[PDB]
Image: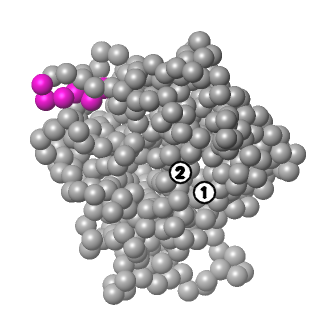
Amino acid sequence: MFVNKQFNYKDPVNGVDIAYIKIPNAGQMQPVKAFKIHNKIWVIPERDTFTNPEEGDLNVSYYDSTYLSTDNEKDNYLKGVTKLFERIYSTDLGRMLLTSIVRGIPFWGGSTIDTELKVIDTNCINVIQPDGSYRSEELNLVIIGPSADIIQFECKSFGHDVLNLTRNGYGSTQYIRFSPDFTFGFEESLEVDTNPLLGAGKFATDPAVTLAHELIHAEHRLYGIAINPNRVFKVNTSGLEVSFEELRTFGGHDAKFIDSLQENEFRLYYYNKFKDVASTLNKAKSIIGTTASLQYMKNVFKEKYLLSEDTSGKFSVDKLKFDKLYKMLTEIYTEDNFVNFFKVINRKTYLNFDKAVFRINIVPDENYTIKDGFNLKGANLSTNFNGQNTEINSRNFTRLK
């Protein structure tokens, strides 16, 4: 259901959901073969050597310039990523998260003429057709291979000359450098109430959790309510800094590092930002790039932001409607609640730096399933979290660094 059709890397482009594309801003990059696995979501099975110029080559942290270079790999990569989305989507939470994301079309704040609505083309990609013509397409999310540092997973946008799209409520297309071929090991934090009967050795993080973690960053950013990367907490451990955004995203006890005073400050801030958006739509009397109507566009953002529209068509931000949306996005969609749903083991806090990288392969149903992840049912790997025991389930994990 979430991805409706089998995509093989070697399938012929068609100009619709399989095509060579170009990421505006990459400039003169050569086209890359991407796949549209869902409305507003694409996957590029390449090592990210485009989003950032300074990182044009693939020359704890893992490096391998040869990684994800063969079509066969790109294939397995496409299937892994797809499998995880399905896994995330199979949970109500994930179903909800993925829904918010598709609805989070980055806002049309490209105009300098307050009475005009206009796209910000860094939120589009050029889809090359079979004839050779290109077509600009809007998209909310792109999943791409990692750059030089294979285990450096992040969420990145293209920013604006003046606007802060990820923090002004507008939003922007998000590019998640991620890989389903690796996972991290953490250590069974043994506490009085923790199950004593826990396998042995270190466990591996369920890759679905890792992806979820990023889609959460992607949600915040798409709705332009991401916490400034500068706001951090000096955790007592000298003193280590950790961004509020990360703590928020991880959720759980870590999210409580953001005191009530900060919470209200952020909530009132973006409430105000959303209001400006409603206000902008109201002043809007014309649109540019007409393959679509003004009304439709206004409605699309009414839906995204959950604005209220009076009989005269005037939009407005309803305080309790906002509260729900904003809460859902920042308090309900957290790594911790995903661990609750997946019922898998994961580090208890964002603070768990444990050197351990394993090459994995969740594509085979013999190793990983949508519903059980590594803790396969009938299998024996489904208890005390055996599936995630790099010892007990040694065959699914290959140490690297």
Q: Which mark is residue 100?
A: 2
Is residue 54 visible in the rendered structure shown here? no
Q: Position of residue 370 (x, y in %)?
A: 36, 69
Counting residues from the start of the chain, the first of labels 2 and 1 encountered is 2
Residue 247: x and y, percent?
68, 50
Say which quarter of the image contains residue 282.
Answer: top right
In this view, the residue farthest toward the top is: 113
For the residue carrying disc 1, how many other residues have a C-alpha within 10 Å: few (<14), some (14-19), or many (20+)? Answer: many
Q: Is residue 400 above or below residue 221?
A: below
Instruction: Confirm whether residue 209 shows in the render.
Output: yes
Is 370 on the left-hand or right-hand side of 335?
left
Q: Amino acid at mark 1?
A: Tyr
Q: Is residue 307 above or below residue 197?
A: above
Name the residue at the front extreme.
311
Percent coordinates x, y for residue 361 in the rendering: 30, 60
- Does 281 sit left or right of 8 as displayed? right
Q: Secondary structure at mark 2?
A: helix
Which residue corresponds to the image point at 17% horizontal and 43% vertical from the top-left?
A: 71
For this rendering, which residue is in front, 314 or 291? 314
Residue drawn at x 25%, y 42% as measured from the top left: 17
Query: Mark 2 touching mark 1, by CB under 8 A?
Result: yes
Residue 151 in the magenta stretch? The answer is no
Kind of residue sitting beneath label 2? Ser
Residue at left offset 50%, top offset 61%: 94
Stretch in magenta:
126-131
